Image 1: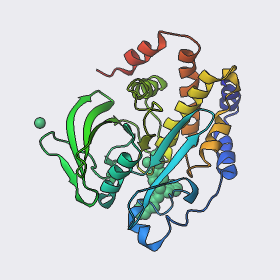
Image 2: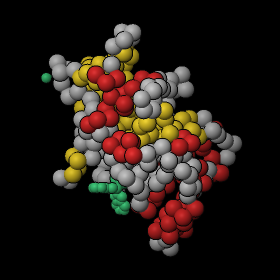
Image 3: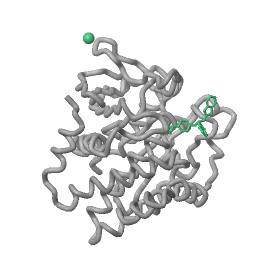
Length: 296
Ligand SMILES: O=C1C[C@@H](c2ccc(C[C@H](Nc3nc4ccccc4s3)c3nc4ccccc4[nH]3)cc2)S(=O)(=O)N1
Ligand SMILES: [Mg+2]
């Protein structure tokens, strides 16, 4: 994996490798996302879920949400990638979380980034100010949160106001990953990834984790590609058989544009190569990433 990396970095050809991927990427219809009535449900007109893998809300008036189910068969993990909720789609977002039985939500963006609005404030910031999404009959409450230097983990309680059933949802919020950018370091990224892994929110006993940034393709694509490559390296006989480009194209069969820049692709290589040390038996790298990430 690093031989390939070193030959690419050596030749300074990441832009060409990345562009080959875009050109070879699947192209499936997004007819439902394009219906006139769903316009105010899409943050960006050039970012849509394919009809074949879009997530359907259980309601009847309209079952559309700009979200895609990315199902990696060999890696044995599913992810729902979605855009940052819009003011009018926060209830839809939590309805999806509820109907798909997700246990965790991974947010890789901030509400405002460099003077631009990227996502609505869909979770409560204060314990005493819970949120009610009337349209979907859901109640959302901030139970507590653990604020680190580059990310925050929140414990939320989501309640179906109809049956009174409640469930705890974990919010993993990476607050320092720049749009069209990369994380500060492989160690800071992997520390975050493994926190999500250790929480149990990715366990198959739950619905797919819900991952989003602003459009649900760039930063979200990177997070998922890395997690999937590491899952594959841990399951196969030979972990050197993992081809990140092939994995990215496979993921791209489910949602368009995963990985928005050549440098995000390169970072993915680096994150996977570093994380491989934990797979190959190094029972100490995990603590090291924690230390190096300087989360306190
Ligand atoms: O790393 C990343 C890139 C982000 C991102 C944000 C927005 C868009 C869609 C946006 N479309 C749109 N942006 C706007 C803004 C105002 C009014 C209407 C529209 S459509 C977009 N398409 C672009 C094409 C070339 C270069 C930059 C672009 N940004 C894609 C990816 S992310 O949240 O998926 N993580
Ligand atoms: Mg307070």
